Image (cartoon, each protein chain N blue to C red):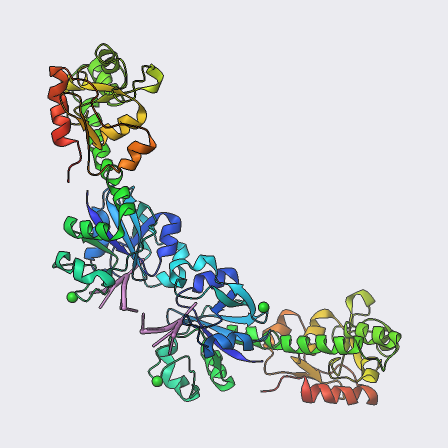
Amino acid sequence: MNYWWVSQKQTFKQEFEGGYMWSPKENKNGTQSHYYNNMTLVQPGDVVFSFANGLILSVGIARSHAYSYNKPTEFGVAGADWANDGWKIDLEYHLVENKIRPKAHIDFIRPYLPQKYSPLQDNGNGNQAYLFSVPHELASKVVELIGSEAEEVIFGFADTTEITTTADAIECQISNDASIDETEKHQLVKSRRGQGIFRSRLEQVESRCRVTGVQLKNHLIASHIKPWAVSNNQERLDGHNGLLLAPHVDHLFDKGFISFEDNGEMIVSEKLNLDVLKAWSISQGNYGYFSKQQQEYMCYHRENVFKKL
Amino acid sequence: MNYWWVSQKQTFKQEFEGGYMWSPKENKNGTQSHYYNNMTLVQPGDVVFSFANGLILSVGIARSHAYSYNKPTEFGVAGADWANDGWKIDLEYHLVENKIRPKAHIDFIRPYLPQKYSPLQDNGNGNQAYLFSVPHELASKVVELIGSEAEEVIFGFADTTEITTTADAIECQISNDASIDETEKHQLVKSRRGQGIFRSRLEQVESRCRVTGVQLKNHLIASHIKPWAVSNNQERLDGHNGLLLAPHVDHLFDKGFISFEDNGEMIVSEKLNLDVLKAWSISQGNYGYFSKQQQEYMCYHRENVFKKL
DNA sequence: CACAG
DNA sequence: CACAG
Ligand SMILES: [Cl-]
Ligand SMILES: [Cl-]
Ligand SMILES: [Cl-]
Ligand SMILES: [Cl-]
């Protein structure tokens, strides 16, 4: 996942109200722009800090690649000098209560500014350009200054999108793989959604939500332990590579906010706000031994899915 | 009539789309602002040049005095530092095709900038403040640069409003004047709209539109020659102080785009675009002698109403 | 160049 | 001060 800084002093209200970013494809004189070319590097799930009137107003999530689109008519005079041939990105804005003023924090972030194409000068004034790459270390510092609301956009939210993208591509690869038969293709695709032979096989091993004890099939998700995307075809359909979980527990486990020790002890991520466990009446403690086959997968989950600092 | 310059780079689209001007009543620190206090001097009919992104985008007509109003919610971050307690004016925007860039013309307008509270610096850069008085000589120069569309907002349009305001006040004075009887009050008020005993008396003198020859009562306006606002009570009800005119001819005569010599020769103002007379098939020439009584009033019209350079 | 200053 | 720069 990448971080971006979009400078929107001229058109923030129009871009926010329309849920987009927009730039020309080239400078007015027809020359290439590093900044406009950055539009073509943004991926769905990338986090975009909106900077306008000296403040960071939004921690946004990109929901498209750049697509060819005319300059928005609603820019009017404020956009007069930009070419009509442009790039648009669908940006899911998340307005923040703590609108940080980066110049007021320049001593804290200066060491983390990139040597080239920095969104800020060494004195903390913004540079006049549209879209800048933000190094991960600089992004961390900005998130520290904004507080919890910035972390809430990123962890188990923005950072899930690239995983979904990867899984979508694998689903395409399976559907076109000549080495596997039609039934296998169908069962592998269903297993991604906890359906088909995977669910029936899991039901021979597990009977309830580990955490909430619910037994009712219509209130349980068939979750993989080793994620579907990184499982091989045998592991994708293995009844021992799953748990039946209530939907909120599925959410916490799938995103690595929780995991389990081999003996069933729940492990809670530092990225899980404990006020979530209180609100949903989920206790820390022991949720029963796992089988040797389940433990092999749970080891993978602890080492690769579970969120650690 | 006064001219104003409103600098709207931060909020032009919101002010244009809402048909308003807005400022705080005081600076953020509670101190008086000359610029915000200018809001309380604007009169209906005053002309306001909108300046944004270095261009004059509108020649507007004020349609209210300033009224106490909260800062528009649609300003958002762009208006964050302004106090919520403000002044609003209803401004009738007229967008111009020729968006002049004053800095590109600074040699032409510099000699006409006021010594104090100028909207422009001597180098042609704008001053950072909201609302500036524009001297009449500076306004003329700006109108010369914009062209016909600016003149069209002012002459026989914006500059009629203060006349209507004056006439409204006189109507109030008449309605409250203890020296005249109820019938007189009614007849004086009706006469302003070409109704009542004035119309009946005019119909004993005139029978047709001087210019178009229409005789049909339902297609004729009873127009004063010496305007109702500056006529005394005898002159307001005098059948010899009027003409029956087709509505377009009433428009041209009432606003002083045309007048007449005592012998009936039509006089055409330099402020009348001749393409109006062509479009409406109105010929220059002679429209019949006026009576001695009518000539006394027509002298007043030529000397005071007729538009001369 | 140039969505900030 | 500060609706531009
Ligand atoms: Cl495209
Ligand atoms: Cl620098
Ligand atoms: Cl008021
Ligand atoms: Cl100066």
